[PDB]
Amino acid sequence: RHSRRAIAAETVEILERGRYTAPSGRVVPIADHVAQAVRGTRLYRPEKLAVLLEGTRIEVTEETTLAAARRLTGAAGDQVACLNFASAEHPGGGFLSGAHAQEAGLARSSGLYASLRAVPQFYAFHHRQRDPLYSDHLIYSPGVPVFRDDAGRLLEEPYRVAFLTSPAPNRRAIGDLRTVEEIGRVLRGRAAKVLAAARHHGHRRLVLGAWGCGVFGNDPAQVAETFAGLLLDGGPFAGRFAHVVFAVWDTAPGAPRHAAFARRF
């Protein structure tokens, strides 16, 4: 936990310095790619994504999001898109505090924070909203360099992925004060918009996972079913992506997040 905090601080200095040192001693430049990702970052408002909506190999694995991205990236030259299980209020989630979360791991391992911190409108919107359902706002971050592996080791060779940043409903704060069906309807609408944005930006390969099933307390089974409804049985995204990985690395005993996706997919 104090190590995460250290890794996060070091990642941030790397983003400021524009270069890092690999285990081999090779000095790796990332300034240009970081700058491109930031300049290419876009905020999509709910009604803009709605417009995109008006216009397949499936794997379930125990990989981290970035492990899956790196495997796909080594296998073909089209840039992979990864879903960031976004905090609605804090870019990078809690990573600089040393938080343990999917988003924090992305922020520690990549240029993602440089992109997200550049979109204050997204965070200010949810701050003012104060509603744990959040919104369909989405940040699209193209060509973000990734330069750490799962253990936190810097990479001899960085790679690039696109991130899609969209917050799942904070079901923990909602409790039973909204129905299972309302939450499901919000999830399905928001997931549709995420897939629409990915497809719109030319991404044929996606890394998804147990979105919102950490602190936010979403039901992994309901999340799996949300994606299945979009991607399978003639759903709106059936056959539109070449490859979708549900990368579900679950630390908890019984790996229940993973189990629900394995079962469904």
Image (cartoon, rainbow, N blue to C red):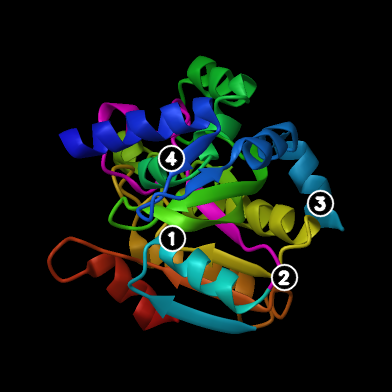
User: Label 3: which residue?
Assistant: 52
Q: x, y percentage for residue 179?
A: 41, 48
Q: Amino acid at mark 4?
A: Ala
Q: Residue furthest left?
A: 253
Relative to residue 126, is residue 23 depicted above or below? below
Res 8 visible: yes
| Cα distance between the residues tagged 4 and 2 | 31 Å
Query: How far across and how far down the image is residue 227, in percent?
Result: 54, 67
Q: Residue at x 59, y 66 (%)?
A: 206
Which residue type does callout 2 highlight?
Pro
Q: Nearer the viewer, mark 3 or mark 1?
A: 1
Q: Which is the main secondary structure of the residues drawn in magenta?
A: loop
**Magenta span contains residue 98:** yes
The residue at the point 36 percent across, 80 percent down is: 262
Q: Which mark is residue 236?
A: 2
Distance (Cα) linking label 3 and label 2: 12 Å
Q: Which mark is on residue 261?
A: none
Image position, residue 56 (x, y; %): 65, 83
The answer to whether residue 25 is left or right of residue 143 is: left
* Sequence-first tag of 3 and 1: 3
* Res 107 label: 4
Q: Magenta part of the protein: which range?
A: 77-102
Q: CA distance from mark 3 to mark 1?
A: 25 Å
Q: How many other residues sit within 10 Å of disc 3, few (<14), some (14-19) or many (≥20)?
A: some
Q: Residues within 10 Å of mark 4 (few under 14, many from 20)?
A: many
Q: Considering the numbered disc 1 on the image, is that residue within a helix, a strand or a loop?
A: helix
